Amino acid sequence: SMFNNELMADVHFVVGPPGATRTVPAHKYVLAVGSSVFYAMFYGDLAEVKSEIHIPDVEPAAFLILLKYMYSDEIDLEADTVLATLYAAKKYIVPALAKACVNFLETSL
Amino acid sequence: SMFNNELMADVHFVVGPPGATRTVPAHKYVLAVGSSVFYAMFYKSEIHIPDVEPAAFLILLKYMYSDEIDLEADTVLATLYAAKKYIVPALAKACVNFLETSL
Amino acid sequence: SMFNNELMADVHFVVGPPGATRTVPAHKYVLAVGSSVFYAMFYGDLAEVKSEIHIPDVEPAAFLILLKYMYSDEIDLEADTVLATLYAAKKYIVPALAKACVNFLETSL
Amino acid sequence: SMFNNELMADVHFVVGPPGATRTVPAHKYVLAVGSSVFYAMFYKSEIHIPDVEPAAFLILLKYMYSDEIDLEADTVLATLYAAKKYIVPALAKACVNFLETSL
Ligand SMILES: [K+]
Ligand SMILES: [K+]
Image 1 (tube, chains in turn red, orange, purple, blue):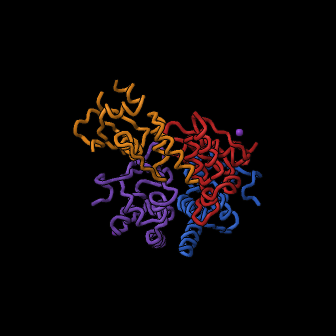
Image 2 (tube, each protein chain N blue to C red):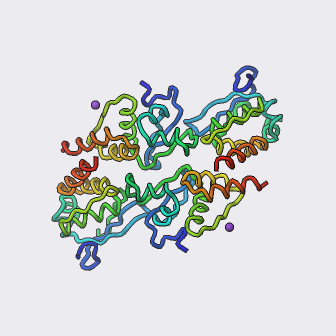
Image 3 (cartoon, rainbow over the protein chains, first blue to last red):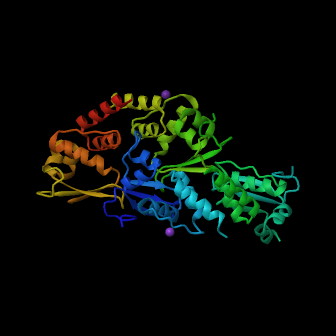
């Protein structure tokens, strides 16, 4: 799979709070197709070329769940990370994922 | 008006990331009655909660003193985190309801 | 001055690359009035309440020049930081500052 | 077509932040003729430039091999940084001109 694969990766995200980051390879095409926010960042008028992008306010597990959905259409939520995933989904304007997080929060212990 | 009041306050919370905190006075009785986590804690007088947003903590406390829930789009996720952290189910339910409505 | 003053500060920016950051207090009102990007971040539909905001891709000196302009209308460029200031000005959509950086680059050694 | 070509390459640059680099072959002669900084350097065969964007470095090199300048909005600032770093004034001028036009 291209998800979380260094093969052809044209961007790396350094995700998480300082001292507890994870570096995630990604593909600008898949991200921009899936999100108006990644589109703006990579293809929009104010896009700036950046090999490495920091996302200090997102949890790594959450970011990987978001990207899994953007590559595969699969939603792989877990109780421990669903709230952080909802933050990421709202942040990048991925509403199908946002909705699934809300339903998950409604129906989980 | 005991909410956020230094009068009779027996606990202070230092809330938020170091360098961007807010100190909030509170009353152990009121918190412990609304929360099993605060009960376990109180039953030190300065408590640091660097993982919680001050704005969310204040919304949680207002609920615990007044039973009033006042949510907004910019604070609901952080309030939900706090409500789950302190096990305040009525406030957590209200946040999830707000979120559903906002979809 | 309210510029870079902890008095009434309702946000703190942790500016710069990891290990070389500076924490800058600021006031959401002044920033949102001066920039559609800070407006979006603080007052817009997808605004999320955040005490501390990280800006890993901006230089601290540059960010302080940007904010000085937003508080005071004064532009205080220097050769050593003008390029990083132009990046910040483009990034937050402050065109009067962008223009001054370009003119400065044109007319400096 | 010696630009970005491993054929005869006597230097390799590891360009960009560690973990997000690109390795670019080059020819010391061509670089040294276009730049006082590269002249001083060459007159080791693997050079790390973690402060430069790969895309910008490639635009700089294309200029140095071909005299062609191909700028875009998303790469112009990073190209200007590189052009100033290696003291390539014609490319720096072109970037500032592009920026002026874009205002
Ligand atoms: K699944
Ligand atoms: K001045």
